[PDB]
Length: 50
Length: 50
Image (cartoon, rainbow over all chains, first blue to last red; front, side):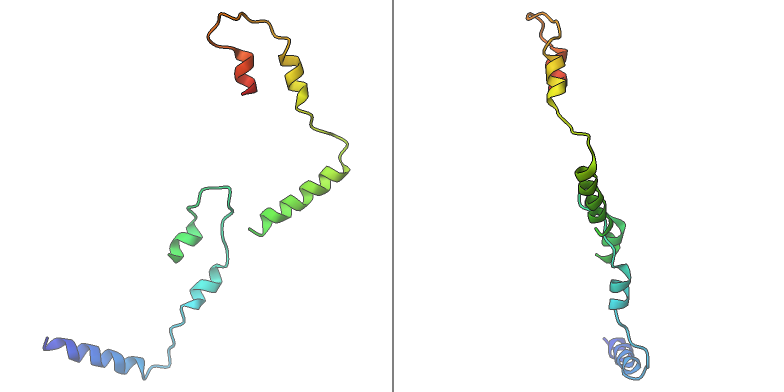
C-alpha cells in the first residue's frame, strides 16, 4: 500500500507528458484480411485479433 | 472473401459459353442394368448411388 501510489502516480505523469500516442487501430486496419467461409472457422488473422 | 466472389464470376461466365451439360441421369441409367442377387445384404449399385 505504501508503494502503490508512487508507481501509479508517476505512470500517469509519463502518459500526460509523452508525445507518444497509443492508437490500437494501427493493428486493426493493417489486418483487413479474413479467411473464407466454407473452410474451418479457425484462421490465424482472426485469432490474433481476439 | 474478395477472391472467392471473383472465382464465382468466371464460373457463371463459363457456364454461359460452354456447350457441355451435366446430366446425372447418365449414371442412373447404366447402374440400373447391373446384375446382383436379391438375397445379398449389401448392394454395390445401391451404395454408389447413395
